[PDB]
Image (cartoon, coloured by chain):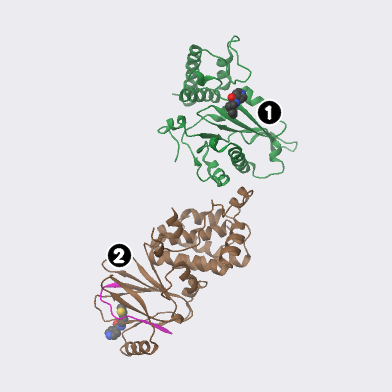
Chain colours: A brown, B green
Amino acid sequence: MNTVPFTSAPIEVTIGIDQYSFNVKENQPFHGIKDIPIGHVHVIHFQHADNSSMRYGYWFDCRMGNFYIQYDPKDGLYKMMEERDGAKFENIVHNFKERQMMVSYPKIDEDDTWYNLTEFVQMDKIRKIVRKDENQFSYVDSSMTTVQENELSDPAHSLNYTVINFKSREAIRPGHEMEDFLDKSYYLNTVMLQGIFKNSSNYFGELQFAFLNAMFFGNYGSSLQWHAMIELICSSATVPKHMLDKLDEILYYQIKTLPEQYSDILLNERVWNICLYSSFQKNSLHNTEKIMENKYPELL
Amino acid sequence: GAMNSSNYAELFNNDIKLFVDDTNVYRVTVHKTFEGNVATKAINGCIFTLNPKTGHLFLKIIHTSVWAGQKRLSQLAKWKTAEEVSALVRSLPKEEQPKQIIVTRKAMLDPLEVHMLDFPNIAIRPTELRLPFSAAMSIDKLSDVVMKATEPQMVLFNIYDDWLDRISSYTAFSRLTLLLRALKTNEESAKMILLSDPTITIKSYHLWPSFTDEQWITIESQMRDLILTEYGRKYNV
Ligand SMILES: O=C(NCCc1cccs1)c1ccncc1
Ligand SMILES: O=C(NCCc1cccs1)c1ccncc1
């Protein structure tokens, strides 16, 4: 079990850690979050009580270093930093625990939610989507735009998701125009899976990461990427059976976890209705279809 | 963006453009089978591809053999249309290729867009106009060449005949659309109006009779009258 200590909490902020969130008051005594489960990526995110705009946060993996949070009064935000002095870090964290100045990551034992949402997400892939190689952790916020979004302006601050475009030369083989547009299997399996992602686990990891950024930061371009990666699978007549089964589990826990009051903006009516009811895979997503119908029958 | 009553005059500027109408590509007769079931029998069709500035009608005949052994023919027809339009553009010299293609039905947009990926600077556009190009098969010479075809075939016509020697392309397009609107709303009457007079001839390479200017005014008036009457009948107004 690992710890992300906080130097202090100068400004009133709602802090999230994965799917949990708590409030800290201005200058409240507070020195971080303990008992964070090893073995998964994690995200620690912030929304200032004075600016409900700009949710922001940091993806990290405690196996990759000792990380702490410190408020910057010049840039006005809670910054993740790495401590290279192992002994100095243990001592800080030991003191703060003894003083009982840390909230505990509140995982229930029966609960596999976070595992299920991050199963294929790997910190090394996040850092290729979010390029800032001097840090072991990755910053994301509500306003960051995607590479594809940019093509339609600052590159250093972009989400480098794999560009999917169903009306592109990459997606359409010359001479197979109609075939490839109505059956995206060759774009999915040859171009994306074999070509770019190398395997389905990396594909699913980008899909899961896009959803999580959409959910936690309201990052619109991530939402577009998540829907696009769902639609590419659903619009393919030929998909490995192991992928369909795993997609159904992936989407089930995403739909399960989505805040009810955000379904209107986070869920694209057209994509979901097409995927669950018109696409080749309309009958391959039984758990996802069952939860969507019982929880958001309005959308459909 | 979409083409409508407001940017109507863009059709007659000097940016090359083409209209594509696919309404006569896949044509069937519906009949009963011996067992009392219903079946279709395809007949030859055509893509109607028109430069509204010159009157150029690239008429691509779609022979029934193209449907042999294929499923979902109404859907295939849209892709076949897009394939043939793309092939036409590729065959044209660069300086004759359109800068825009306007499709008369929105369902042609994705098929043409996909077939034209090699021409990213050709805009594919829909229209809000209710253009009557489906009535093209009411023009006898066009119907005749489509039905007689025994193989795929592209046939050329000037759908304006020689009109542009005396009138503008705006006026020529308005006359053509009036003629086709009439033939669409009441083909028999429309045709009676155009051929009533045995003394007015149709040139070998022309589709329409050789009316003087004054005779065109009488004709156009009579076509207008036809269209409005039929409309009163339609809606009981
Ligand atoms: O409440 C305590 N633990 C911090 C957790 C927090 C709960 C909600 C936001 S911060 C506590 C109280 C007093 N002295 C030491 C520890
Ligand atoms: O002027 C004609 N041809 C060249 C202009 C065009 C090019 C393509 C279609 S019309 C023409 C006229 C009458 N009948 C057949 C052809």
- Coordinates of residue A50 in the picture (x, y in percent): 26, 67
Quadrant in the picture for the C terminus of chain B:
top left
Instruction: Chain letter for mark 2, please.
Output: A
**Where A177 falls versus A291 (above or below)?**
above
Q: Which residue is mark 1?
A: B147
Q: In front: A71, or A119?
A: A71
Magenta-drawn stretch contains A165: no
Q: Main secondary structure of the magenta part?
A: loop
Amino acid at the residue labelled 1 = Met
Give, as a single range, the part of the protein colored magenta. A1-13
- Residue in view at x 57 percent, y 60 percent: A233
How many C-alpha atoms fall within 10 Å of the one at disc 1: few (<14), some, or many (≥20)? some
Identified by mark 2, the residue type is Ser
The verdict on label 2 being within 8 Å of ligand 1 is no
Which picture quadrant has residue A97? Answer: bottom left
Which disc is residue A52 wearing?
2
Chain of the residue on which disc 1 is drawn: B
Between the residue at mark 1 and the residue at mark 2, the CA separation in whole angstroms equals 69 Å
**Looking at the image, is A294 positioned above or below residue B44?**
below
